[PDB]
Image (tube, rainbow, N blue to C red):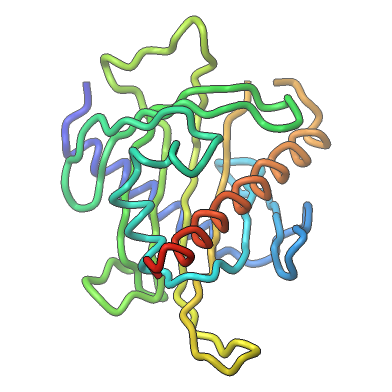
Length: 232
């Protein structure tokens, strides 16, 4: 039964944790994607255990992806087949909200369908991770699992635990092979899921990398559709 100070405090702490972790040095390569520079990396973080990070380029402005992810969270099932449901429980100000989601199982059948109760904070950040009003170095949306009365674990579904995650977007402007000057986004996603298995870290690591690579396909299709329809 948390107060709004307590929710905001946890969201702020979670956002700072995800920003701190996503910008750590010295990651290990788990798996590379099809497209040059797409990668899933891991490392050990004290307090959290093994964290995964995706890094790839998305051919749209960082703002466009920020606004979609931030404002259009309930529409995630519409272009992402892995999200079966997305409901906003409560928006509590300063970019903080509570959400409910049901995720599909991984393509390996290692990660089963599960549901989530997530506390989020979306913000514009500076390069040293301070919240700014404009001219962002990067855009963040952090997630941590919490308990909300009215959203108990279902007997029919595993209640997943997000210990820390985020997606993080950094604007780029590139020169195409044609010589056009075009905005692109460096896209990073942090994942650190408290899985109830005794599954080898061996197999967890492949299953997690696969999920991460599988997601970026759907992000790119969403972007390419959006460019076909002249929206960017």
